[PDB]
Length: 108
Ligand SMILES: [Zn+2]
Image 1 (cartoon, rainbow, N blue to C red):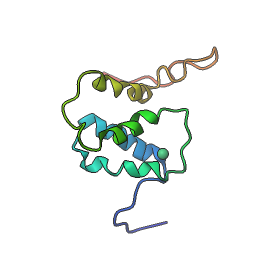
Image 2: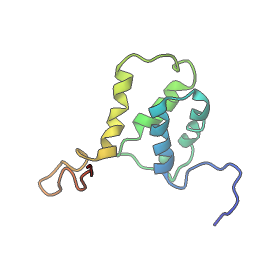
Image 3: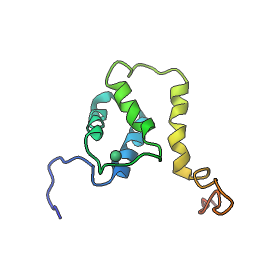
Image 4: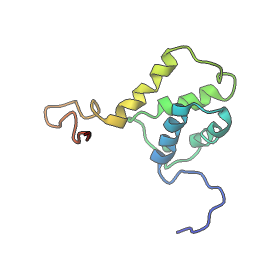
């Protein structure tokens, strides 16, 4: 579609921006870039619930300067509720049909 781009938002697919919300939390950088997360409350698809977006989207709103300060401890554990998807071990576990894990990690 488009060849040249100056600075457009990532709304084509929530995943990309949604992954941006987590990747951001990983390194925990200033609330500068973060500010492009507030725009996600406007348009996106729109993305539906029942997946785990409140976590990454509520954080951005709760932050917005002021909260940048050093966190306590639970905060650090909040990032793990999104981390569960990165592995998808418990995601399937529900009924007696699908397996807890589909693909296993390789290591030598
Ligand atoms: Zn979205």
